[PDB]
Image (cartoon, rainbow, N blue to C red; front, side, top):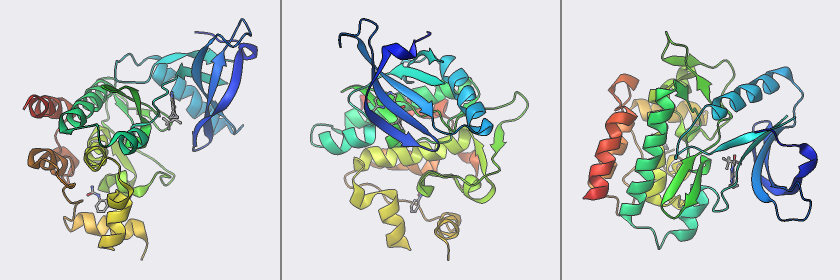
Amino acid sequence: TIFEERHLKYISQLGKGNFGSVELCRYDPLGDNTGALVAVKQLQHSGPDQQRDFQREIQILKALHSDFIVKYRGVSYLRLVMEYLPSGCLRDFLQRHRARLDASRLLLYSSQICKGMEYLGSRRCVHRDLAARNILVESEAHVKIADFGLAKLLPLDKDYYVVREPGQSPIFWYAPESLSDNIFSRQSDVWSFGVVLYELFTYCDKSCSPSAEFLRMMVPALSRLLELLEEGQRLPAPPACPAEVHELMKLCWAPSPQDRPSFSALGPQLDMLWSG
Ligand SMILES: C[C@H](NC(=O)c1c[nH]c2ncc(C3CC3)nc12)C(C)(C)C
Ligand SMILES: NC(=O)Nc1ccccc1
């Protein structure tokens, strides 16, 4: 669980976001290039706010044990060591393998993401940044939730979180209560999950992406988006989307957070659709 920095060999950049980077490294204590590959997250900001957030991120991921959550491996002293999943993010996987993945497969991914989120909720963890770009592909038939950089643990007596600073994620995954009042909860995660369902069933095609649809539907973008959503406007059924899948999307997009189904309620429904 403790990795020596001298043994972590830099290979390439895997991603960035906020004030951290993820690097592909080889953990190579023999120094002969035979060591295993790992993904390593580090900060680039000395600011105590970020460092405290990163410390919290590590504690959260360390305590998460799920087949559907990216595996914590350890730390180096400053760096968070995780498993490396070469298939990359689901967003890119969907775009690339579009012609191989049928509706059953998409429903399988949906079910696995749902189960991870059900576990996350059981730990009082709000993810806050659920999106296909933050889901990793373990194999053809196995996805895992990643990117816990914005994740928060809910106090025992409170089921929601209010953030001071404005969000920095693409605005089309945010629940209306997050857009308007910076309110995040397990139910705003459900809203975002609705958008993930949309991404899955569009195969993250750019031309019908959440952004592309908003520019079509048409004063600040965030205010406009809030208005559209308040009016009851929603993303359209993806091309060839099963009706039942689209219905579940719309339920995830219930305007009031209390009217959205829970992940535990969504799970059996997705399993039923996958079997059917
Ligand atoms: C860069 C982040 N990646 C990670 O934290 C990762 C943890 N293990 C990984 N394995 C592969 C990848 C390829 C997609 C680059 N990313 C990660 C994010 C979740 C946003 C894709
Ligand atoms: N949840 C949802 O429907 N979001 C949305 C609506 C219109 C345009 C872009 C995104």
